[PDB]
Image 1 (cartoon, each protein chain N blue to C red):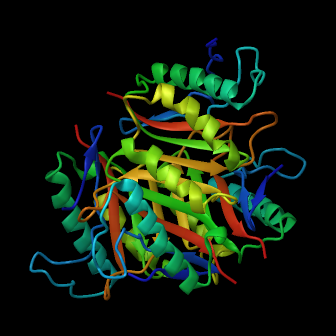
Image 2: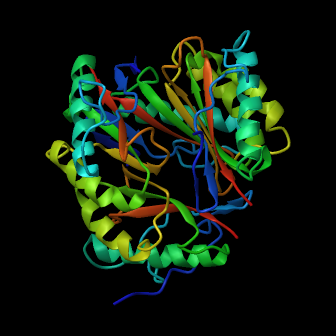
Length: 119
Length: 108
Length: 108
Length: 108
């Protein structure tokens, strides 16, 4: 089961600067305003739904992503996230890619930000 | 919480120009940056870190032109000590924020 | 080689402060900075990029105290355009170098 | 080629997969990545730091396709501790270098 994105607000849209899109940190918010339900892979799918939306608004896609940074509270959780990341960046793989332990907002287990070319 | 401790490092989340009561410092980018540094003081001390133990700092701002002003303040809390690394990034800040700073620090 | 290009992005090698004649440059940290900018300018036009399409710069610097000065020079070359991201970092340079500079750039 | 120590932190230069003998090692990327780690072992232990004290690693690879391999290797030494951050980046390497790691580590 895939899912629909949260509506994009002013602050969740990211910013476009000299032809590059810099998404904000996209968390696994549903269109309710609630952390989606599941283990960490389900949250990751949601983060991706949210990525796809703000990419699309800004005139970008996963194919023009040139960097993606994964935030998580525990580096143990990386492998499950990367399991999921591989379905979206598959035959395209962003040239640079960081994972980085961080305080997430309440009930979030994963946040992703991406830099992307706006053709 | 204002961050996470892992493996003797502290990783602050971004501090914005709020007073302790939570009302935004309505004032120019230098006034705001002082308040951000005052929030950094507290989260650092709360974690058993200090300014001296900051090894990275990352500045988020709307316009790269506002760096000179932020730096003139950065350099008053970090003068005898200068973190070894520092990034500066253009970003959309929360409402009325002109500056936001994150820090990585050693917890001794 | 000095560079690689992926997904339309030029990812430059660290440009140290050498003259075209092969020799470290004759002076203080500004002159070095200038030379690194003259050097970078050529590696960029070669790639289908320019200063105007730079999006990140990493300043490797020997002594973080001298950034005020590297930055006076960064301002000259990125005057109208300022890249949206940059980092400064302390590092071990080739003997005699006080500064080295990498950029990420767009190749339209 | 040494690396740096500041505010109790080791900042390694980038370890390519060379033997004790100056010789580029005989292998796939998996065998290479084991040599890089051999050489990280050394410079880490000379600096006053172990693999357990690494707070960040960065991997340079010439093809992002080979990351799932390097990451398996990575897994063996960064097992019961994982560095709190890591990056991976496509850059150019020098000779028959598929892989290249620098790292940042605590010291006392």
